[PDB]
Image: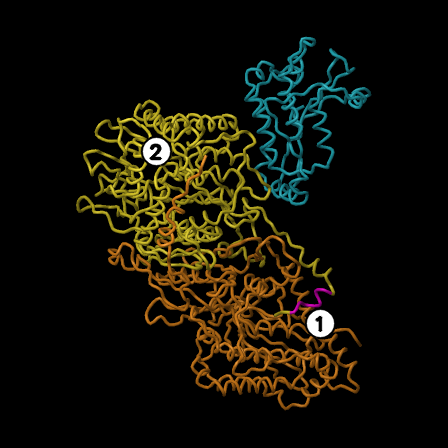
Chain colours: A orange, B yellow, C cyan
């Protein structure tokens, strides 16, 4: 009745010596697995020995005030609310209306996103990890900066970002208006997909920002100013002329000073948005945030911003514009962009796969209301098709059913090349990926898919093929999913646009 | 980092009314998502509204004694040890050798695996759940059984399982030999992939079993007896014919009777394998086991077993066999099987993608020796090509560099269809998947990939495209990984096959 | 109707093991009155005994609330043997379903429950007839995803502990006849309404 000792405890040294393997391979590095048969070099591409692991997926976003068609919009009701808060705290006759104050209050958001963007470029460059070779150059390439310009001209970069914080910090914006705090939370922060040391990184970069473009008696028109994309090796002179183009109409201007001083008198100095200062010791560390990951997982990309120089055959006058005119819609702030654009004046046939009802996927089984409504923020569903003009139209445009305080334009992923010299590879994609009929892009699409599934809460993919004439649905792993129709997402969007632009109590 | 929004606390009623969402969709049935754009029916296949979540992945295995081509093998060392304990330390009989006793002990394992197989068939059929409509019919289809037969003949199935466990008690086998405990624990458990309510289920099913064959004085074989596959719809009479065919050459053999009485005398009645009885109240709930998941991840499917009726041009004598002959090879037990067979007389050229070194990734950052040795049990790496007997040969065969106590032949995944009946779909696949150049293979392959990535610790895939003449490597989400070469995995296989066939009930090493 | 069918075949099984020197009506007259061939339950006792348990197992695929006393009343009625005077060789009352409600789905234009007639007291039906009746009853229920969604919803809403549990029987399971003056007060002042009307009537 005596249990004898097992084999593994009778020879523990044999077990511990056979199983001593080197784990924790550094990412940012090409790995060749080698051959197990070694005669298989006669089977050249039929044997895959490469092992590339990506590190950065940058979510490329556009900040939005929400959808707006009339004065009953939540941005216009918020303009009314904040204007009667500011006007009833400032003694005197104002010269600006409610729409001028809300357009100022959105231009200040674009300034603060610019400051967080250049401060992110600065604070990324000091990150080092031996087991992550993507730090810091892949993060800098994903933000569209030349990485050597930041190391060579470090003091000039610090002066530029501190001067942006000084010159944009001269304007006042309410701190208890969570739009600024949310956009700062997105633009300041590196997010791991998993709480490990060799984790993949998510970032948020603006695709464009809103430039003020004063018009006079015919109103106010926030225009797009495009940010540099990943792969552009932009230096400090390019970010300087971008900052100078963003502030050329409001830096030494009297109306912006009057509106800023009125916001500074209405909300106290403790009630203003504070810009972070940057020294040579400022570092942002990658943090684990499941709310970030939840809204990245349910993000749906809407496509490229339509510009005034963008050529669209059957769609004239569809450029993205936050407008204001007393002649149109009784002086309401108007913003209703059409989606499904990518440049390239033709139909991107893959956006037809975005016409299904989305799947909102969460982990676990108990979901609070705050988690559910935070996971739907980057989600945008199409509702109808935009109507062309001329009976000859190459692209296909879509109107949404509302959207949050930001929309996703793109995702950019940074991995290592499997070919020598194993430099960084840059892949830009929507949720919808078209795979045309050529022998080159099948293995390339499979490499993009295997790269994407390394990211723990990656956005759900939709893949269409050329010869198949067929889209495949959500390429993602689901745990506890529900199906969202456009009306539920529209209600959540209206609630969250109202909550971001909310002012405190007094009058 | 993100102070919480005070608007949500001041208006929690609006937040609760806006986020009342139907989560916990039961898995096992088709769901349509609908249309965000109502006019998108004009773009018929360019809009996907289907959602087919799979439930069952059955791992189809072959039980092995390890690789054996000389007397220095783990199975031959175990044969020597158990023959010394049975024949000499206890007064055993002298009409049989060590290879005969070891092949009796190997033939008993197929009986134990068959008992666990029909016991899992019986325990599955009483499982019904509102949250999982795959239960129990998809598990019963994946095991090869007609699911209406086990419902209509539940008492007959339930008593046949007990009769198998009773008639297996005519043969004695040692209980401290953890080979039997491992195979019984594998082929009976229902293994859940994530430990949630409607998670995915992994099973282990024998592809074949080893049937005992006596050649008289010129040796002793173990030949393959194929089990039913996941579309076969086999009744109880087929499983009774299989069990009668398995114990046909064992109950009338007096060599087996002498060896059985010798093992009974040497180990005692208390130290034998006891196949326990089941009653009508016997249920198996699915369990969470991260060692099983670490086995299923990094598993390597070796292909179909080769039979003596299998047609392989250029390879006439490559059927899988556990053979001993006193004239041949010092009287050693020989199991040297060729791998890479796909059940057809041609080259499955996706097995060329199994010729690179494997990746073994584990959860976390601190892996114990027990965890690393457990996670490599179903991994099998090819080492060389087999030499074709001639110059014309359509299939390409592979010799391994050792393997564990079981090799994976296949995986069978059960899912629901996306077309209008929405029935159960049965797909069988290797780790290697060939996507031939055809207009309908890419979307089907993408549906296969998306069904596979629902399973958490799934096997790593290797996809070959015929249009590109190019394979892609391990299609899996990685973690803390290593690169394994053939000698390291061979050393781990040597360690585990030595530890499984060790009987601590013996008087060895004290 | 599933629960009533389970209590019906469970009473058929529990009756056939009852033999008494003082009452030679037991068990054949009770088995004839239920519509069953009494030699079939004797010759195929293990098959009957396992079919009753399989009915109780396959009924557990559907969730139904246990505090709804409709189910408890019908199960208590159609399983008991009720004695009329509480003496040794007293008279026996039973309750047998004339028909059961079979589920019918018409799609978007509605949903029916149609009659499924049970065997009458001269019919001499074997186990295969009761198996055909049970297969005809759950035929339109196990393949319906409306029923699957509603079953999962009742399971989620009430929990597994708050569902109707059809309990298992073993070979030692006996029903002795009981004295119940509430059942007798139901049988007294009962009013027979006549035969059910069928679509072929």
The residue located at (44%, 56%) in the rendering is: B367
Q: Which mark is residue A502?
A: 1
Q: Nearer the viewer, mark 2 or mark 1?
A: 2
Q: What x and y, as percent, mark residue B467? A: 33, 57
Residue A392: tell me if it is visible: no
The image quadrant of residue A282 is: bottom right
Quadrant where the image shows the N terminus of chain C? top right
Residue nearest the observer in this picture, C118 or B372: B372
Q: Which residue lies under the disc numbered 2?
A: B105
Residue nearest the observer in this picture, B126 or B39: B126
The image quadrant of residue B143 is: top left
Vertical relation: C161 (above or below) B20: above
In the image, A473: left or right of C159? Answer: left
The residue located at (67%, 45%) in the rendering is: C157
Residue nearest the observer in this picture, B493 or A407: B493
Residue A446 colored in magenta in the image: no
Residue B8 colored in magenta in the image: yes
The chain letter for the residue carrying disc 1 is: A
Quadrant where the image shows the C terminus of chain C? top right
């Amino acid at each position: 009745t005596r249990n004898d000792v097992a084999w593994y405890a009778r020879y523990p040294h044999i077990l511990e010596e056979a199983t001593r393997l080197p784990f924790a391979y550094p990412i940012g590095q090409y790995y060749d697995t080698g051959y197990s048969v070694a005669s298989a070099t006669e089977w050249s591409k039929y044997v895959d020995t490469s092992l590339t692991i990506p590190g950065v997926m940058c979510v490329n976003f556009t900040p939005t005030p929400g959808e707006s068609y009339n004065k009953n919009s939540p941005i216009n009701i918020a303009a009314q609310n904040v204007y009667t808060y500011v006007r009833h705290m400032n003694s005197g006759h104002a010269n600006y209306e409610q729409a001028d104050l809300m357009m100022y209050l959105l231009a200040m958001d674009s300034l603060y996103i610019f400051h967080s963007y250049v401060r992110k470029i600065l604070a990324i460059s000091k990150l080092y990890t031996p087991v992550n070779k993507y730090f810091p150059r892949a993060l800098l390439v994903a933000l569209g900066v030349d990485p050597e310009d930041v190391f060579a001209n470090q003091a000039q970069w610090e002066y530029f970002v501190n001067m942006v914080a000084y010159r944009a910090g001269a304007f006042a914006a309410p701190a208890s208006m969570t739009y600024y705090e949310r956009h700062a939370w997105m633009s300041n922060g590196l997010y791991v997909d998993q709480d490990v040391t060799r984790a993949q990184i998510y970032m948020f970069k603006p695709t464009m920002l809103w430039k003020y473009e004063n018009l006079g008696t015919t109103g106010t028109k926030l225009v797009p100013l495009m940010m540099p994309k990943a792969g552009d090796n932009r230096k400090l002179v390019d970010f300087q002329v971008l900052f100078n183009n963003l502030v050329s109409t409001m830096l030494g201007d009297e109306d912006f000073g009057i509106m800023s001083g009125d916001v500074f008198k209405a909300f106290g100095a403790d009630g203003l948005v504070k810009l972070l200062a940057v020294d040579s010791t400022t570092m942002t560390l990658p943090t684990y945030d499941p709310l970030i990951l939840a809204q990245i997982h349910s993000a749906r990309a809407v496509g490229a911003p339509i510009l005034e120089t963008s050529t669209l055959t059957g769609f004239p006058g569809r450029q993205w514009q936050i407008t204001q005119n007393p002649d149109v819609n009784n002086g309401a702030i108007i913003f209703h962009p059409s989606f499904g654009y990518d440049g390239q004046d033709h139909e991107e046939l893959s956006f037809r796969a975005m016409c299904s009802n989305m799947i909102l996927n969460l982990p676990g089984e108990a979901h609070s209301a705050e988690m559910i409504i935070e996971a739907t923020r980057l989600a945008t569903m199409f509702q109808v098709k935009a109507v062309p003009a001329g009976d000859t139209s190459k692209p296909v445009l879509y109107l949404p059913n509302g959207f949050g305080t930001e929309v996703v334009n793109d995702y950019t992923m940074i991995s290592v090349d499997k070919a020598t010299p194993h430099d960084l590879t840059i892949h830009t994609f929507f949720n919808n990926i078209l795979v045309p009929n050529a022998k080159e892009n099948y293995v390339a699409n499979l490499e993009l898919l295997n790269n994407i599934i390394q990211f723990d809460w990656a956005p759900q993919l939709y893949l269409t093929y050329g010869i198949a004439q067929e889209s495949f649905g959500p390429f993602a792993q689901l745990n506890d999913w529900t199906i969202l129709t456009g009306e539920t997402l529209a209600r959540m969007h209206e609630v969250c646009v109202t909550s971001m632009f909310d002012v405190p109590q007094m009058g």
